[PDB]
Length: 293
Image (cartoon, rainbow, N blue to C red; front, side, top):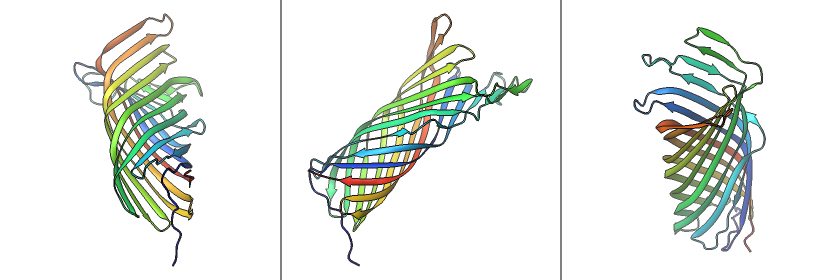
């Protein structure tokens, strides 16, 4: 018993990089605006895609840390997609449902510009607030799969590997939050709780078999998330850590634009005929190095 303490100083620059698993689930909604009734819902799962996060952290002052983090899809990954439509106004049970297990998660990425304000600090604890800006992007392509239309009056399979629906989402937002830190010998744990009432969501939908594109753009959606990690200082300058991330983007609502691909001609439809939501977690492991010159 006689351990190894982190070697931190003011004006430090820190760099950390981790890698692991990205998972989550998005929704693509179509409503009747007048009645708020759901005429469609697309469910784009995400199944362990391999990611790579990276952290960069100048703490100019001891009570102040600037931060630029982000992660990216390492390559096309494993997804899924299900497509429901409630076509009979007089029926709770949806009438249409296609399924596309062969859904590719083309790519995924996020960046996060964050500042941390420490209001209280001693040698093992820290508490403060954070403010920042995030943007997050997802891309899928559902291919093949099967379908039932008209409550199964036309069951069947799609052509293996043919582009069916393409879909991408973007969630941009300013955020604020509470931050805590706990050290002790060669251990450091970081918890963070984040929130926003000012999410801006966009999505794009190509139905290639209908030759139609769709534009959904949302403002004022709500969001909440957490970042927690635990690490050990293997040296005074190096911390091996594991890290969990969660992000919930609440359904924002707005209008839909429809472009007819083979005419160009476009048509816009009215408020809350569309929804855009998502749900994240990342499990990630790596190493942090602190320089501080």
